[PDB]
Image 1: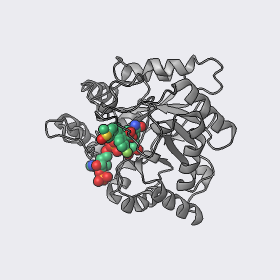
Image 2: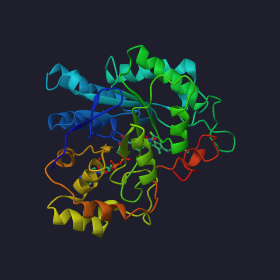
Image 3: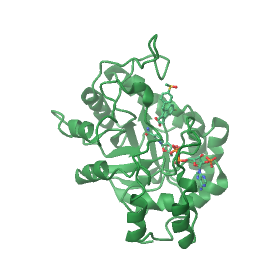
Length: 318
Ligand SMILES: NC(=O)c1ccc[n+]([C@@H]2O[C@H](COP(=O)([O-])OP(=O)(O)OC[C@H]3O[C@@H](n4cnc5c(N)ncnc54)[C@H](OP(=O)(O)O)[C@@H]3O)[C@@H](O)[C@H]2O)c1
Ligand SMILES: CC1=C(CC(=O)O)c2cc(F)ccc2/C1=C\c1ccc([S@@](C)=O)cc1
C-alpha cells in the first residue's frame, strides 16, 4: 500500500496514522473493544473526558500493559480538555483526572476539545434559562498557555487543538510568547466534508490533521433519515467493490492517503479488525479526486447549541 504506519509530529514524536475512536462506545463494551483493538494492531486510542468512558478504556489499556501485549512506549493515547475546564486553574486537574481514569502517567497527545470555553461546574453544557450555552471569559490563548504548562510538567508529550477554524489556528500560531506549536488539529473529515482549505493550511504549518467521524458517524444521536449516508453511497461502494474492500475500508484509506491520521470508532470486534486492514491496498489518484468530488460541506458535529459563542468555529469559511 506504500503506507507507513506512523507519521512525524512537530514535537519530534511519531503518531500512528490509524487510531480507535471511543465516542459513543458504551462503558460496558469499550473495555473489550480496546482490548481487541490492541490485539489486532491498533496502537493509538482516541479518548475524551466528555465521553464518560475513560475509566473503562483505561481498564483495557492497563490489562494489555500488564499482560505485556504491548509496552507503554508503543502506545499513543490521546485525550481532550473539555470546554468547562478552559480556566487556567482547572486545566491541570482536568488533565490529571483523565490520566487517573486512563491509568496512565502521561498522555502522548492532549487536545483542546473545542475553541469554546463554557462556565465551570458539574454540567458539561451549562445552559441559561433560555437554553443557550453559558460561556466562560477565558480566551483560547490563555488556555493554550495552560496546555503548554502540561508539557513542561511531564503530564503530556504533545499538545494540540480540535475543531479550530483556520483563523483560530492562526491566532495560536501568532500568540505572543508562543512556546509550543499545536502538534495536531483534529477535525471532522470525510467525502461529504473534505476540508481542503483547512487541511492545506494546517499542513503548510507543520500541523498534522486528524480526521474524525470518517465513516459519517452513523450512530450520532441526532441522525435523521434524510441525511446523506457515506456507508450507503453507491458511488463509494462501487470504488470499494473495484478494490475488493469494504466501503468502510475505503473511507478509512481515503484520509490516510491525504497524510491525515484517522480514528474510526467501533465496539464490534469483527469491524475493529476489518477497519485496521487498510494497509494492503491503494486508492488511485483518480479514486481520491472522485471521493473528494463528493463534498457537500455536510457536518455531523456542528455544535448547534453554541452558535452564538464568540469562539464558535463554523461561521468562517474554513
Ligand atoms: N470533537 C471531536 O474532536 C470529535 C468529534 C467526533 C468524533 N471524534 C472522534 O472520532 C471518532 C470516530 O468518529 P465517530 O464516532 O463520530 O463516527 P465514525 O467512526 O465515523 O462511525 C462510527 C459508527 O460506524 C460504525 N462502524 C464502524 N466500523 C464499521 C464498519 N466497518 N462497517 C459498518 N459500520 C461501521 C460503528 O458501529 P459499531 O461501533 O456498532 O461497530 C459506529 O456506529 C469518535 O469515536 C471520537 O473518538 C472527535
Ligand atoms: C459534536 C459533539 C460531540 C462529539 C465531540 O465533541 O467529540 C459530543 C460528545 C459528547 F460526549 C457530548 C456531546 C457532544 C456533541 C455535541 C453536543 C451534544 C449535545 C448538546 S446538548 C445542547 O444536548 C450540545 C452539543
